[PDB]
Length: 262
Length: 128
RNA sequence: GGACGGUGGUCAUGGAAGUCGAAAUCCGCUAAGGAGUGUGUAACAACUCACCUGCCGAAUCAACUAGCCCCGAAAAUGGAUG
Image (cartoon, rainbow over all chains, first blue to last red; front, top):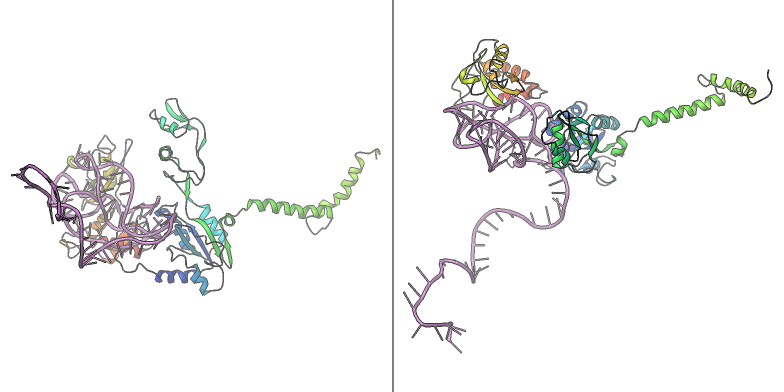
């Protein structure tokens, strides 16, 4: 901080402030900015700062144990699964629910051009089409493994393709060429490692929150209710017209294979 | 960022728009109308430090009374504190009331929320 | 591996503008984020770095004191502590 000379620069003082801050809030989430820039963090911090707020510290961040030692639960060093802190983590303490926080943080991420030597967080692709750039070193794009040609006196990318896969490092040359193209693939913000609320520990697979899949299971589950409702004949309001026909359909049917005309 | 300085309403000065280039990147008296149609407001007074960006046959300028100039305009004082940090050569003691209202125009561009925070910057910058 | 904005920092001077010389070193916006450590062009042009973080895992650094050795150490007919 601004006090650059030796005076604290605290141990137990900030950890005590961090202590009351866990004890103050129902939900504590542990998150990664490391991908994110400085301003970019402030603006995500700004949204959270209205709702209820987040802190950084170092090993003084591991002291989820002292808060737990104060209360009775299981969000700490001891009872937890494997402490989900990773390097360059902060702690977000909140009034806000875990699912909602995940959506807040995960859903709205800020786009940010890739970096040389950074591992791609997701597949990076280039689109086909004219760059609009005149003839020059098109060769650099080919070196990168982007097929290119001059069409109509302009350098154009021949076809869409994945330049690099997820988990693979982005070469320097690649980054530089993607940047010239104006391509901004990566999404940065605070990644969620874990959330604690009310005696339970939630991991990022939980927090990315399915949600269409229940709309199909609800519609199917309602169709399971509805099905049961038409065929069963059990009529309070919905089920009731569908049943009447089941005695008639079965009869109307009974006319079709057959050999009365009446 | 490439520095031009201006006094309210001026155009074409040989020492100030020639060896710093004619912005539009060719053609002084594009920028020489374009600055003058903006910066003819109140009388020529104290100088703003005024900032050029040049694009493909375009000029564009950032003036936002460049903070030392916002203080300059609120004060009515044309220089800055000389023998420093202590007791000015000109007489420019800014009011408390001047310092918030300058900070209020600064308050997208000190990226800002609070007044009592953006007051500190300008107060450190107005007593330095 | 992270550094937005005030603001191309005030003086001075062809000229500093982080980076000739000299004020001055605050803060909003922030989880970290100095008006900056060395490389620049006549001058304009970029990259790293303070601080903070990861990876690593155990000692580290500062400083006094002391011993021996090493160094300073070139000569005359042929080498030795007898």
